[PDB]
């Protein structure tokens, strides 16, 4: 057999895993997400290649929050990875480290921040929800600090807004909550589901900064308005993400938003994209729209379920290889050379209609 | 079994009812309407959600013509409801009352204004056609006044512009006409079909105001021009509605018109939408376009035919629940917060192309 | 059985007629035309109806070149109609007369101008090609003058630019050429096919005016440029027509052109549309775009083949009835009331985006 | 049997040839190309025909780099043509000569420049890659000069960016490299695949001009920017071409680029189009967009495989015949008359919306 693309792991994982486990990842906690996310939007962006530029050597390295990484391609959090494969987050952490990139560990990981750190050196971010008990937030942040984690990826939605639920077997737990002072008991899983705060505002983002000095990334910004508020709130970065609620027919376009968000941020902080990135051409398109990098979630868990650590390694290498080739075809020798003029979007004014210069 | 959406009652009603009865409601008196009304247009409007706004408590209450109601979702007139279910308009009136909203009673109801009122307290509107005999109009208006009705919903078309006709059985009549002085006889049904006035102009809207002090709602306005004329004619509100004539290939877009009509009305009077509202996301989209509320017709009759009063109650609760969730996902805590900037339409100038501020 | 629409005669004629005869009419001399002409374009024009206008009495009468007719719907030339039905042009002439409209007689009719005139009073136009022998043109024009014909419909293409050919049986001929001085013989059919002039320019349109005082209509104008040249050349009217060459993938849009042509003509002369008009809504749309009337070709021959004179009568009555209803639904009491603001086209600036007045 | 169009040879060649040989030509060295290239884009350009212009005599002759040719239709290089038919490039050269047009000989031809020249008089161009060994470039250029070739068609990509490979049989070689000094051996095929230079820049285009006085054509320009750089680099012409990489989902539009490139070039040098030209209407559309001519590649090899020299002759004659007819239908008597106003593109401002003149 031979796996040739990132989306081909999706079938192998469907087979390998119990239906509910696969659906939980493919479609999220509820059945709200689509697997075809952004595939149409990405399709409708075309390239404007430059020729006769020496691209024999492509540099795709970049810096994220001061940390040098090998490619603008990072790993998004997906919860309880030991459900997907016995090695779980351990495998994700090792592959990320080996590929020279960043892993974000889920708040709901089946492995703790220090377990992840025990695997060796690597730059890691930690997913945080603001829980109702602010002292519990405090304990999570401190544990992640001690484990050497570099940034907070703040998720700002509620996963409560069902059919895709399963139980963690007794041998597996939500390890980041294990051992923490929770105060004055229907199980640990129920606690972390019940205690997500429904009243979150920007004031809470500012509060986070009184308990930690770690850079905070705010996930979910889809508008110029919230991009400005993120900057003013002291966010170190923005993640443009929103998987949608398909049963409600609630679709927001992240891609259309990406450029708007980037422009609003005014170069103050980096802007990342998370959602349906599957091709090297997708990565290129997001960066040309002005994103500083992207995150992939589903492809990592699927390839973990399919081949463990070796599969994650392979997904990252395929994405990487297509990205390099895309840059080469475009005439771009580094990330800096990936300009807005290397793509064309449906909302671009047609260049063929414009008068050409020469006075 | 389990009904999960508003449009799922449509199948149960098809089964339960004789073909002609169902077609009469699904497609109107003639075969001119489409059941897929506005579904495509609504599909092509996307959301612009705001984050980090406390939406734990959503207020969706509003005021319509001075009357407080629990949600911007009201019931449209559908004729002779005892054909759909033995309790007919009685069931519709009770469910509307219980849900804390407004019912509009059809001019052609199988139950009179006072029967409807006998069921208890509730804000109700009455559908009026201007009949050729102006004294008959006078009697209908006075009966509705006496029964405690609050507003006239003036229908301005002729339902004469066939294959979907049935007879009312002998035990059922057009109760609003029963007992009235009709003057100097081929049946009551033929009278109310024959005596609709074909010469109606704005002068007739002004005439209505000499016989009644009730606020008049003008149904059918699809243009800036007629929105201005409605205001100048003394209308208390506008209903943007037009089910189309599909066999003639006569399609007008109500949705495109909604925003135009609202803008033309200049905030003077409320603008409502009637036509193919089925989802909480539809309700949200109409309000963001500037409508003050919406009416649903078909879903009410269908759920009446399927489950009686309990079905209407259920349709209203489903629409309501999806609406709240839509507002929550959008970052809107009240109706006032549902601004034009919370949606994006195909005719909107692309924000991603605009230069972002910061001088 | 029951025929309900204009395009339903198309099947009956397919059955009734030999394949080659039907194809010749459906697809033209060669296989170049499409039967679906303009159906998509017409589909993408929507209505902007006005309400509360008294439309109980619709006047659709108009004047064409000084001649009063009952409706802006006229008959286009289709050749050798005795192939389609034994009564041929005689039947077309009588039905046109009875409906109170204009018939254009084909240059290639199986019945002469005076035969057509022998059927009784009626306003008729004659199709002319400029033949290489200018003296033959002279004879055709004079015969048509003598027969009481009112205008020249000048066709300016060459039908030579095959698989859809048949022979006229011996009892049928090209009657307009019969008896004329042709000078110094492979048959009459070959003569009229061979002697169409390939060198036609606007100078030839001006030449026509030295041999006749009849108003000349120029068929085929698809651009602002040729509309201006038609006016300057002394044309009394323009017919916007071009059936396309589908095998060559040579598509020009007449509909998009219609408005452009009308605007260029600056109200100097009337503009007509010929090509795929089948619905009352089509007629309305062409007039709102600024055409003074339309011609129908295929539907006339088909209904002739299907039911003779009675079928043509029926096609005209169906088109007429749908047109009236379309005007009624639009709030238009006469042709004068059919303004550009009663439709919306894909190239119209969206009114919903504009700011509404009230200073 | 009867071949009626250019794309009908595609099936006959599929049958006649081994799968790998056909795929290599249909889809290129790798499987990256699409056979449907530009077919959709060309479809969405419509005509604006002019009438009453004498087109009985169409002149389609033109001048390319000072050389008079019979039509703006030239032959693109396709490698190793003896794989497609025993006579190979000999057949292509003779048919081009007979049709009075230009052939470009592939760098990878199974026949040398002097063999091609031995067939008789004809204007020919030679495809060049810049190889790592600049002295080998020197030898190729000199051999082509001596053989009477008129221009360099510089290919600037690398065909290395697999499944569609075959071996040349022992009796066939890459004849342009045969006998040349290659210096200090795994076969000739491996040498010419391995020694393509990956570091090419505009400096190399300028270097070409120090070793030859032949006009250089630069293939691959897709942007205003590279069109300007081609002019400044001393290029004698630009070929707008890019077959895409479909497996990578890497699509650039050549057609949209064509007009932009032409405008940027400011009339300094000719602009040609290569890629999916199959119809006379395609040729017309490219010229109206401002191209000076086009090249066809696939249709030539296919018709060679199907009927040898007689097939190429036939492809050229079909393209030619449709082109003439297209010009005739458009009202264009020469290439000069093919203006930008004879087509309409999706990016054109709608003329129907503009106000017509007459002050």
Image (cartoon, coloured by chain):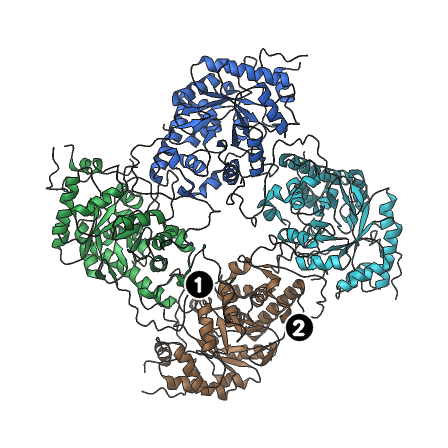
Chain colours: A cyan, B brown, C green, D blue
Image: D331 above or below B174: above
Front residue of D68/C114: it is D68
- x then y, percent, for residue A334: 70, 37
**Residues at discs 1 and 2 both on one chain:** yes
Q: Where's the N terminus of chain B, which quadrant?
A: bottom right
Q: Earlier in the sequence, mark 1 or mark 2?
A: 2
Q: Which residue is mark 1?
A: B252
Which circle marks residue B59 in the picture? 2
Could you tell whether C173 is left or right of D205 in the image?
left
Q: Residue at x 84, y 46 (%)?
A: A116
**SS for tag 1?**
loop
Answer few, some or many: residues within 10 Å of disc 2's Cα (few below 14, many 20 plus, some between 14 and 19).
Answer: some
- x then y, percent, for residue C227: 32, 49
Q: On the image, which quarter does residue A122 sit in?
A: top right
Answer few, some or many: residues within 10 Å of disc 1's Cα (few below 14, many 20 plus, some between 14 and 19).
Answer: many
Could you tell whether C37 is left or right of A149 in the image?
left
Residue C111 in view here: no
Q: Residue at x 66, y 46 (%)?
A: A286
């Amino acid at each position: 057999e031979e796996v040739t693309n990132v989306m081909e792991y999706e079938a192998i994982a469907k087979k390998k895993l119990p239906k509910m486990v696969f659906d939980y990842y493919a479609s999220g906690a509820e059945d709200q997400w689509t697997l075809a996310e952004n595939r149409n939007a990405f399709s409708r962006i075309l390239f404007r290649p430059r020729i006769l530029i020496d691209v024999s050597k492509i540099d795709m390295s970049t810096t994220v929050l001061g940390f040098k990484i090998s490619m603008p391609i990072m790993i998004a959090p997906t919860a309880m990875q030991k459900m997907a494969h016995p090695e779980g987050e351990y495998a994700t952490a090792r592959a990320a480290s080996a590929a020279g990139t960043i892993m974000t560990l889920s708040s709901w990981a089946t492995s703790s921040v220090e377990e992840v750190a025990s695997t060796g050196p690597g730059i890691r971010f930690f997913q945080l929800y603001v829980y109702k008990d602010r002292n519990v937030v405090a304990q999570l942040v401190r544990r992640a600090e001690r484990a050497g984690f570099k940034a907070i990826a703040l998720t700002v939605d509620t996963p409560r807004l069902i059919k895709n639920r399963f139980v963690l077997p007794p041998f597996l737990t939500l390890k980041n909550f294990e051992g923490l002072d929770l105060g004055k008991d229907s199980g640990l899983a129920s606690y972390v589901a019940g205690q997500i705060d429904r009243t979150l505002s920007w004031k809470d983002v500012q509060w986070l900064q009184t308990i930690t000095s770690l850079p905070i990334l705010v996930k979910g910004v889809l508008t110029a308005e919230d991009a400005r508020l993120a900057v003013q709130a002291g966010a170190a970065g923005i993640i443009v993400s929103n998987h949608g609620a398909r049963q409600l027919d609630y679709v927001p376009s992240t891609i259309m938003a990406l450029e708007e968000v980037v422009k609003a941020a005014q170069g103050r902080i980096p802007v990342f994209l998370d959602g349906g990135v599957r091709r090297g051409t997708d990565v290129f398109k997001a960066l040309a729209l002005g994103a500083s990098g992207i995150f992939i979630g589903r492809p990592v868990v699927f390839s973990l379920a399919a081949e463990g650590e070796a599969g994650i390694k392979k997904v990252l290498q395929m994405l990487r290889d297509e990205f390099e080739l895309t840059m080469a075809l475009s005439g771009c020798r580094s990330l800096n050379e990936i300009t807005r003029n290397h793509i064309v979007t449906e909302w671009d004014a047609p260049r063929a209609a414009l008068p050409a210069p020469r006075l």
